[PDB]
Amino acid sequence: LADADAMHAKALADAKAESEKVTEEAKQDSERIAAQLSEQAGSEAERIK
Amino acid sequence: RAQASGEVAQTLTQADQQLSAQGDQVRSGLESSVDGLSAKLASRILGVDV
Image (tube, each protein chain N blue to C red):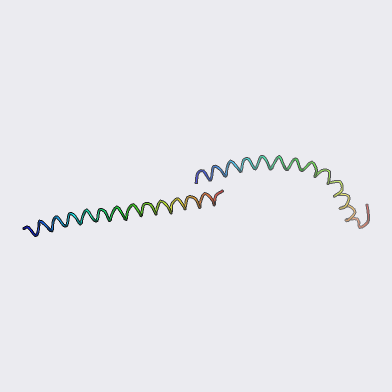
């Protein structure tokens, strides 16, 4: 019972850690996608003028 | 995109106006040079000095 409680606490800590690893991946992604879409916007604006 | 298109359209309108004005301005000297051009063309299609 104590081992299972400790494993549950470790699982909650590991869930907090993947929430971190979801923020680290998702913020970096969102930033990169924003970068490529801004580059696409600039390229098409340059092409059009 | 929309700004690029709007800027392009505005510059197209301005350029149309400016280039039309420039063309009719230059057509004035065109009508001066037309006399010499036609004289030389006549002196060519005739094969001798006009």
